[PDB]
Amino acid sequence: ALSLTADQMVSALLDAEPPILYSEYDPTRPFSEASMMGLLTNLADRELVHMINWAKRVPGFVDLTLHDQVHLLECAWLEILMIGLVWRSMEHPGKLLFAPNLLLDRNQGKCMVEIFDMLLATSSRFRMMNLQGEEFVCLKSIILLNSGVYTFLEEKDHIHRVLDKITDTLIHLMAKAGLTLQQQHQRLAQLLLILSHIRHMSNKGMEHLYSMKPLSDLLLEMLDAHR
Amino acid sequence: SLALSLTADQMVSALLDAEPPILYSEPFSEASMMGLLTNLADRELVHMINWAKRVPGFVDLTLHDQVHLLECAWLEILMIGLVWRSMEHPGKLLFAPNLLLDRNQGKCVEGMVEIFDMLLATSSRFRMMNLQGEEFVCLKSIILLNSGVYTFEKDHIHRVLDKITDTLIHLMAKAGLTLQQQHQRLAQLLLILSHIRHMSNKGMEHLYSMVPLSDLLLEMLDAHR
Amino acid sequence: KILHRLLQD
Amino acid sequence: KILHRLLQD
Ligand SMILES: CCC(=C(c1ccc(O)cc1)c1ccc(O)cc1)c1cccc(Nc2cccc3ccccc23)c1
Ligand SMILES: CCC(=C(c1ccc(O)cc1)c1ccc(O)cc1)c1cccc(Nc2cccc3ccccc23)c1
């Protein structure tokens, strides 16, 4: 991990990209609050399995103990799902693309509207900033490594060393894009500030997830992780 | 708009000058430690409001936008201030100079040891990074402007945030950090905000579960609901 | 809202 | 713990 260059970081990250899963959405059924949220739980439940194996392909994640890996995922799983949702929905203004067969807007949304608008705002932000896929895979990896690091004698310094390299990697991409030295700083800050709101959405979402405690076996083992 | 026209040194000297003072507090019980905390927070709120008004660019915003940003980040700001005060007291949280508490004295009240440890963890990280006051006042201003910006103009707010970014980098270049050391330090600082945001949400969560509380605190609390 | 009062005083 | 087990397999 610490020996990987910037281009080998991006390539490894891009190659680790999980697929986009489909929904069991039947368009011949006007969704309800229980119907639509059932599709989302089922989708997230299948997405989790891919995220777990995506994590193992994230540079430095395997170097950590089995104890710390569980911790990092329990804290950041909804953040990674959300930023992934936001990423897919970038080229669909006013809409959230939960799945290729599941495309909802604010009107249909909350078939709950507060968190919808936040995800839309975040997606508009990426659109306005013209977020690149190489930048996205970097941010998503950061979330996995940063969200649970200040929630742990013991080795936390290595995680910072990985984060620092992803920072360099992010800078290298902006430099290889022709941005000035000042522009690289500002954009880097703009990106990481998004993570603050991604954290916010995940918290408000998690808060709504144990409000209705729609529940699979893997989700419940992570819904108690925030309780 | 004044703020944008400022230079990085004139930005630091503006933020350092707008700094709120450190207020004081009045074995503990549950309602005792909480009661002192809500009293302290309510008095700090008035100073925060006047600190916000002296943050470059914050007055250029509409009264409605000022309310939104403050309603969204008030606890984050109280928290990062707490973390900054407790930096020279390892293992302890300095709510007030006459109110110094640690992990075991912490609890009493239901949970609040988890978030206590998060604050302590947030207090050790600055210490490890040797966080400067010039950097601290920049982080706090960012929180004020960033936390509620994607919850609404075109802005402006992003333009001021960019200036605070340029200002942070200036401080790091003023300290002899290499070009690579600047990006990394910038990243490390801005990632703390994600955790401060998290702590705020878990603390706000506990606040809505309950102490008489003031009408001002109630308005800041009814914003997250 | 009290916050309005304190933001104008 | 499913997550712990799934990190193995
Ligand atoms: C943001 C949507 C969402 C997801 C989810 C996660 C776990 C779960 O058990 C059920 C849903 C989700 C699904 C797939 C992804 O790729 C990313 C995220 C979620 C998470 C927590 C709370 C809510 N709240 C909501 C309730 C009702 C309607 C909503 C409409 C839009 C957004 C959120 C809604 C959703
Ligand atoms: C981190 C302390 C905190 C504050 C607070 C904010 C609003 C309020 O109505 C009461 C307390 C606070 C006070 C002054 C400051 O300068 C900064 C922050 C807060 C916020 C939410 C929940 C809790 N609960 C607790 C956390 C940690 C330790 C505790 C010990 C005793 C009682 C509650 C605790 C605190």
Image (spheres, coloured by chain):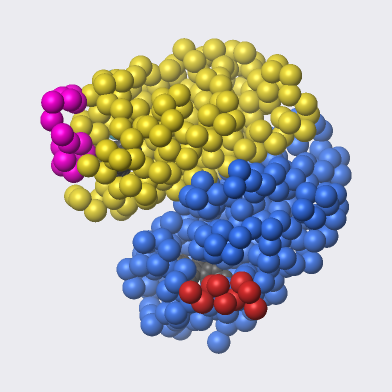
Chain colours: A yellow, B blue, C red, D cyan
Q: Is residue A17 above or below residue B156?
A: above
At a point 81% along the width and 33% down the height, the residue shown is B178
Q: Considering the image in quadrants, where does the C terminus of chain B appear?
A: bottom left
At a point 51% along the width and 23% down the height, the residue shown is A137
Q: Is residue B216 visible?
A: yes
The one of A217 and B1 positioned closer to us in this rendering: B1
Seen as rendered, the residue at the extreme left is A29
Quarter of the picture for ligand 1?
Answer: top left
Q: Position of residue A75 (x, y in %)?
A: 40, 42
Q: Position of residue A216 (x, y in %)?
A: 18, 36
Report the magenta residues as a range: A24-37
At a point 51% along the width and 77% down the height, the residue shown is C2
Residue A68 placement, left or right of A30: right
Count up the numbered dots.
Answer: 0
Q: Is residue B176 above or below residue A87?
A: below
Q: Position of residue A27 (x, y in %)?
A: 17, 25
Residue A23 placement, left or right of B158: left
